Image 1 (cartoon, each protein chain N blue to C red):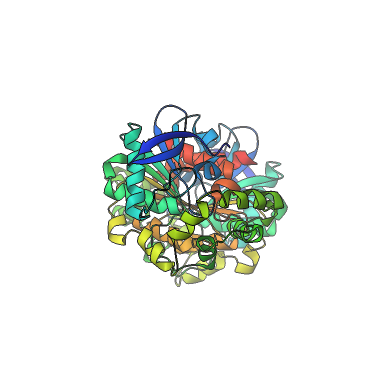
Image 2: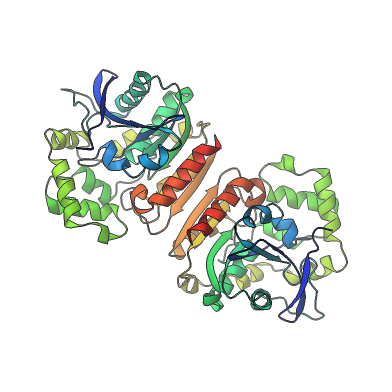
Amino acid sequence: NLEIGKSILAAGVLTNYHDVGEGQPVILIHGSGPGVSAYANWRLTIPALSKFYRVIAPDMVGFGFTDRPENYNYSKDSWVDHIIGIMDALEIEKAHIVGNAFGGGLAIATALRYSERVDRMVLMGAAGTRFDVTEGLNAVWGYTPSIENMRNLLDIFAYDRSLVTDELARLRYEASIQPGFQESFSSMFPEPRQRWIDALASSDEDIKTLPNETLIIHGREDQVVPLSSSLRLGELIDRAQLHVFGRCGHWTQIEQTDRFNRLVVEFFNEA
Amino acid sequence: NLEIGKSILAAGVLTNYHDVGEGQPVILIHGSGPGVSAYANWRLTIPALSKFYRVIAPDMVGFGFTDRPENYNYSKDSWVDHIIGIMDALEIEKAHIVGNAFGGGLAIATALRYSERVDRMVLMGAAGTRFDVTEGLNAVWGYTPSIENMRNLLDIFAYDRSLVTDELARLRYEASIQPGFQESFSSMFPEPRQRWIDALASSDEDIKTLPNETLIIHGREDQVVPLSSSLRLGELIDRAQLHVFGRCGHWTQIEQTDRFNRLVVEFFNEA
């Protein structure tokens, strides 16, 4: 199983992670969803970035193959603690961070609590602002296992539905039912879900204080996180650039892979 | 005077233009403003692009050193005729087009009337949609010569006012008072100026028909053409990407030169 990488104790949690490349460190933080993991999210990104950077992609607690602590309290602050714990464990004093959706919210939160530990940030279809719950988001967080339910989620994520094959739906469904996966995931964002979007968000006031060079990326047709949210981030963060991909859904790293990889590498190259 | 380049008859008008590089043709269309010319607008762009493309940058009729025909009727359609005439004169059957503001409006209009002659488009702080007249735009089109009036226009264009030096204001003022320059410019967009923004614009319906891969660029702080206009273009054009530069005014090719050049070259490289 390629989703299984290396193991390390971080913030007291046995963590599954991938570490490829050499040089300036870049932390990739995956999004949220049933069966999501660092590999599933970044398999097409790591190869490109690792040619110029040291790429670290961990499975956040509660997701992938990282340990799922008994009675663990899933929260924005605890997830930020995990990210910092991973960096500490690997002696990563400062790093660039790429956060996808849920992970984008965590990236912002990490940069706010540990500003000196974060250099440049790439926020993709990122959580981080309070936006009204969408049916797409409620469908993802409210997922229960079935190939049809997974097919719907994939449809929700994709701009080009022809990419949603029976095989992909089957494989992602299987990933979602691995031991303890659905259990931890379903316990994370129970109804009403607006509470969790708000909990993952950072205040306008705090976001405005971010000094980091930031690249905000969003798919025009994103059905999960509205484009308006990234437009808002683009107005709040001072040293920000906004790049919107037309004909692109919620996972820009998959549907606009080459463009995304090029933009990210060049953005970090400036540093 | 480096603003003076080569001369060629195009659409019956003796035209001043620059032609550098080899390979795929790229037409650069400058913006509008007192003393504006192709060289003044693209001096920092041509060098970078000409390394991979054949770059053609003409002075649009009524601007720069191109002939100013007596009783000439300055209009969107006549300017489009000039662009096509330039391409015809140089045996350029199809080309990518980069349009800055006023030039962006012309690029859209050219792609609509001569779709087969246009490949990819880059629209910067582009005219093309009907946006409410801004004080910045009225100040530019309503300019009368003076170093102080030019200093104000430069301030209006720049995000970083420290770039507006006495020397630059002096040099641009001198360019604005060359024989016939202010005369033709002031005759172009007389009050009420909303009429001309509307005349340069293309309908939502027409814009939606554009099949071209398009890159829309805008400076967040643009005081001349509102960011909202490019956001609108980003929703209307199907194969579009929107890139907004924070800490950037109306002339992105000057204040975000390296980033702009990199984005444009890579965008054309995809073709």
